[PDB]
Image (cartoon, rainbow, N blue to C red; front, side, top):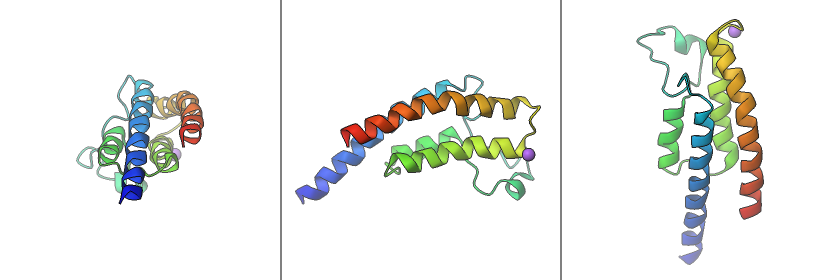
Amino acid sequence: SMEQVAMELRLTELTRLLRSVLDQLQDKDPARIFAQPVSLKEVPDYLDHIKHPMDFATMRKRLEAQGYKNLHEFEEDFDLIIDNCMKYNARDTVFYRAAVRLRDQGGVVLRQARREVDSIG
Ligand code: NA
């Protein structure tokens, strides 16, 4: 049906916008601390600590399958990246501090993303 097609075009345009958001967030991580999953070969104890690992590559896979239905879902995964790092790593570490700086800088990007999603529909 045409109504199904129109819903599919909307998901496609959300996907486009979330790709630009994902790129902008990821530029805020020039060290590439959050680029890839934590390897269970190098942090064997990770999944004892962190129940829902997340990283930018994982998000990009989901996005490319149009797997985010709304901005809230995308934000959930971005918050996992930050919040997982802030739990596993101590305050005095480069990892924790990188997560704080990503959260702060990413707030800007997500604030306008929300306005664009609401405005375009
Ligand atoms: Na901790």
